[PDB]
Image (cartoon, coloured by chain):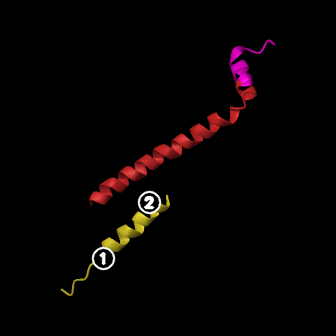
Amino acid sequence: KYLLADCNEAFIKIKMAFRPG
Amino acid sequence: ATAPDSQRLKLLREVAGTRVYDERKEESISLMKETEGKREKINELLKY
């Protein structure tokens, strides 16, 4: 369960990106 | 004495002291299968 959790905040941190546009 | 055979097997199983082990193991199996689903999900998302 805790490793599943770890993978979840991994999921949040990989999706971020920076577009000045 | 007139109690049928199923609880006779349960009785001797208790005498063996393993009357615990059944409920422990089927308590384990459900958690095992749900963690199988979780870790399979981990593998496809790992590919992602």
Chain B, colour shown: red
Q: Horizontally, is B41 left or right of B17 in the view?
A: left
Q: Position of residue B44 (x, y in %)?
A: 30, 54
User: Residue A11: which quarter of the image?
Assistant: bottom left
Please tell me which residue is depicted at 81% across the width and 13% down the height of the picture.
B1
Q: Is residue B15 left or right of residue B31?
A: right
Write the start and end of the magenta stretch as one range: B1-12
**Is residue A1 within the magenta segment?**
no
Identified at 30% across, 76% down, the residue is A16
Q: Label 1 crowding class (10 Å Cα cut-off): few <14, some 14-19, many 20+?
A: few
- The amino acid pointed to by label 2 is Leu
In what element is the residue under mark 1? loop
The answer for which chain carries disc 1 is A
Same chain, labels 2 and 1: yes
Badge 2 marks a residue whose secondary structure is helix
> Where A8 falls versus B30 (above or below)?
below
Instruction: Indicate the position of residue B33 as horizontal and vertical percent values.
Output: 46, 43
Q: Main secondary structure of the magenta part?
A: helix
Outermost residue on the left side: it is A21
- How many angstroms separate mark 2 from mark 1 (CA)? 20 Å
Subunit of label 2: A
Residue on which disc 1 sits: A16
Residue B29, compared with residue A21, is above or below; it is above
Which of the pair B12/A1 is nearer the observer? B12
Q: Is residue B9 magenta?
A: yes
Q: Colour of chain A?
A: yellow
- Residue B12 or B1: which is nearer the viewer? B12
Marks 2 and 1, the one that precedes in the sequence: 2
Kindly identify the residue that appears in the image at 27 percent across and 58 percent down: B47
Q: Position of residue B45 (x, y in %)?
A: 32, 58
Q: Which residue is mark 2?
A: A4
Q: Amino acid at mark 1?
A: Met
